[PDB]
Image (cartoon, rainbow, N blue to C red):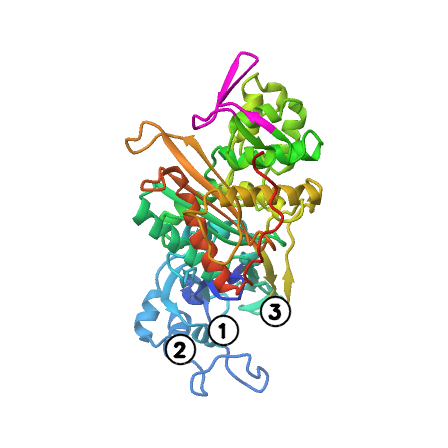
Amino acid sequence: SRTTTVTLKARRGKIMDTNGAILAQSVERYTIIGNPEQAQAFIPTTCTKQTGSNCHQINGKPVGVTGAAAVARLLAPVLGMDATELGAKLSISGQYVVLKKDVTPAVKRKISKLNLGGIVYAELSNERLYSNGTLMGSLLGGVDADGKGVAGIEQMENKTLTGRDGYQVYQQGNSGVEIPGTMTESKDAVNGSDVTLTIDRDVQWYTEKVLSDSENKYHSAWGIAMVQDVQSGDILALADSDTTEAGSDQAKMGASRAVSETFEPGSIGKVLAMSGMLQLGLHKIDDKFTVPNTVTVEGQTYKDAVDHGNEHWTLAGILEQSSNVGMVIAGDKMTNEQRYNFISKFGIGQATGLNLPGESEGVLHPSDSWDRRTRNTVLFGQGYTVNVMQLTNAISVIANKGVKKPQRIIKSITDTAGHVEEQQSKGEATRVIDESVASQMLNAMESSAEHYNTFVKVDGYRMAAKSGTAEVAGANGQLTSIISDYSTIIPADNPRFVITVVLKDPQGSFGGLTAGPVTAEIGEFLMQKYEVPASSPRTDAIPVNW
């Protein structure tokens, strides 16, 4: 016979930052719906000693009418509406009519007590609020009108956040085995679980502020920045210079540029190739080279960015001076397979495993597809592409004693019982290089940072860092566009964070090195916020020249 199923919609879980600060949450309100034809069939049950409270009454007396009129009389005082008007809405044709919008959970509960299930039901609204407004807006993403996550973290964590709808089934007809209105089965909703990010609201806010202030100062087409905890691989901030309200159409339009952008890393990429050279025992970090300003190999000519003479640099100095030519000379005996292997081993060309919507794996071509030139440019961060997360994780390897961890952005999930379950990214920690090789590269990176210490400084702290530039898609009247990138490990003598900044077409007195001072502004804030002890004096510098 006739049957009616009512959906009990699960309420969406919250998104919170690393400290429990709420970033996204849904408003529990309801639309109250009537079914006119079921209302018209309604006959109220008279309270007697046989029914107990399984009956209908108003002020302790029978309802006195039937159908729409009876439903309206029962509903009117609960909804604070006029019975005549309700009766008219329930006297139309069809199985659907809105009776009242935007009612509270308390009113919804009162309606349930009227013993009108099947005839009247509540539809949970899907309004989603983001209390921090524009903060990490495109990273949070947004939901559609049905409360489904369609961008950012809302989408990635949608299963967890959505929960599982329940239902009620009513016999509204006359089967002869239950009376009309009897609820014959139900299944409770399981409300969504809450998601805690590794992102810290204060670090994220300051990083976005630094990028905004940097746009005012240097007028970059865009800037992105990331802060990663060295020992855990947790992401404390992942930021871009665009400004969008969380949950807005703009935010839902596309992933954060920090998530999606890919680019050649340029000279920062030398860290990966050189690590390989040391690991394989092809060179030692203090090996001495004579590095001319050009070199020709197999009909191919390579140049450094700047004219110099025949320089007396060690392998560490080739890194510090960003010498492409030095890398070509040093890498002479490194086979194509070894080159590919060490770049790939640092995570280049592979998914971070974070599963951010719109995230690319980047591009690193198989070594047998390389030609006589690209087999060499790969040594200095050209001819393959990375996103900021991959670059930052590769640099973290040097900070973390040669070990690469999967990065994490989802810290924990809290279920409906209130149980907090820490989350752990798929895939395991892997050793990329020996700890001793990592130490030597950190030492060379600290010499690389000191190369720029006339304008890149965090007072009281040693840094290990590398800079780079690379051509990207030309824009805004620039014949050739470039990015400035810079990645810093801080403090060098007890690494705590990696901070990477990428700016497109920065202007001003620092030109292509503008990303450097920007990482240092973030660095300064982090040492103060976490009260990091000042560095000890550097006593073991590996020589950069001879």
Whether tag 1 and tag 2 are in contact, CB under 8 A, the answer is: no
Residue 418: mark in rendering = 3
Whether tag 3 and tag 1 are in contact, CB under 8 A, the answer is: no
Percent of width and height locating residue 177: 63, 66
Magenta residues, start to end:
289-310
Most distant residue in the top direction? 299
Quadrant of the image containing the C terminus = top right
Can you identify the residue that label 2 sits on? 78
Quadrant of the image containing the N terminus = bottom right
Q: Nearer the viewer, mark 2 or mark 3?
A: 3
Q: Residues within 10 Å of mark 3 (few under 14, many from 20)?
A: few
Q: Residue at x 41, y 61 (%)?
A: 130
Q: Is residue 294 above or below residue 531?
A: above
Amino acid type at image mark 2: Val
Can you identify the residue that label 1 sits on? 112
The answer to whether residue 341 is magenta is: no
In 3D space, how far apart are the residues under numbered discs 3 and 1 (Cα atoms)? 26 Å
In 3D space, how far apart are the residues under numbered discs 2 and 3 (Cα atoms)? 33 Å
Q: Is residue 378 above or below residue 99?
A: above
Percent of width and height locating residue 9: 51, 61
Asked whether residue 95 appears in the rendered view, the answer is no
Element assignment for label 1: helix
Element assignment for label 2: helix
Most distant residue in the front direction? 546
Residue 400: mark in rendering = none
